[PDB]
Image (cartoon, helix red, strand yellow):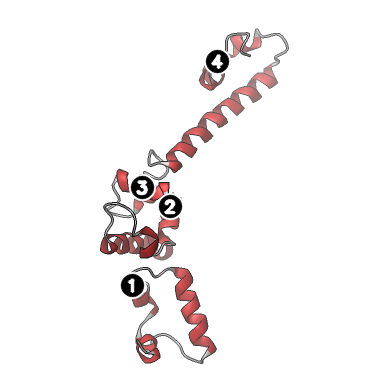
Amino acid sequence: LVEEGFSTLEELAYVPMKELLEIEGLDEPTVEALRERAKNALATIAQAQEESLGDNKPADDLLNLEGVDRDLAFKLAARGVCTLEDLAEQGIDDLADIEGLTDEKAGALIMAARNICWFG
Amino acid sequence: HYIGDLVQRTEVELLKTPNLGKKSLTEIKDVLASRGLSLGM
């Protein structure tokens, strides 16, 4: 694949099927499987980074609790609190070290998360 | 401070307290039940 000029997962995911079928030893089923794997790899990479910080996964799930700014969602996700369920399971004591989160604001966010997850 | 104070609180009130998770609420219920007590008396 690298000798045929492919350097990125994006090229393999999006390049016209004809160019991948010009490679010696690739059949239409193997090219389709390679593209599906490349798209799934691209999807997984994006989701992983979005859950690690606050790009999309924690910027929607962890940030569901009213009051969560994007910065706080990334601070929560850096502690492994990636979802609104993960936040509903926390104590105030587990979040007390997050810069900009007061015990009252932590308690309000955990209660908002519990109201949505357990009482919605 | 007392078991009599705890028994008067409802489950919904205890879930509003700071640093009070679903796991700690289940522990409190299981322990009160072992003594024949229930929350909200």
Q: Are marks 2 and 4 on the same chain?
A: yes
Question: Residue A108 at what x, y percent from top left?
Answer: 29, 62
Q: Are labels 3 and 1 assigned to the same chain?
A: no
Measured in 3D between alpha carbons, the distance from the residue under mark 2 to the one under mark 3, in whole angstroms, is 9 Å
**Chain letter for mark 1:** B
Asked if the residue under mark 4 is in contact with the one under mark 3, i.e. CB atoms within 8 Å, the reply is no
- At mark 2, the secondary structure is loop
Calculate the distance from the C-alpha at mark 2 to the C-alpha at mark 4. Answer: 35 Å
Label 2 chain ID: A
Q: Secondary structure at mark 4?
A: loop
What amino acid does circle 1 point to?
Answer: Thr
Q: Amino acid at mark 3?
A: Lys
What residue is disc 2 on? A81
Q: Where in the figure is residue A5, as x and y percent of width and height?
A: 58, 9
The answer to whether tags 1 and 4 share a subunit is no
* Residue lying at 33% horizontally and 61% vertically, measured from the top left: A112
| Image-quadrant location for residue A7 | top right
Tag on residue A75?
A: 3
* Mark 3 surroundings within 10 Å by alpha-carbon count, few (fewer than 14), some (14 through 19), many (20 or more): many
- Which residue type does callout 4 highlight? Ser
Q: Quadrant of residue A88?
A: bottom left
Q: Foreground mark, 3 or 4?
A: 3
**Marks 1 & 4, CB-CB < 8 Å contact:** no
Q: Which mark is residue A7?
A: 4
The chain that hosts pointer 4 is A
Q: CA distance from mark 3 to mark 4?
A: 34 Å
The residue wearing badge 1 is: B17
Q: Chain of mark 3?
A: A
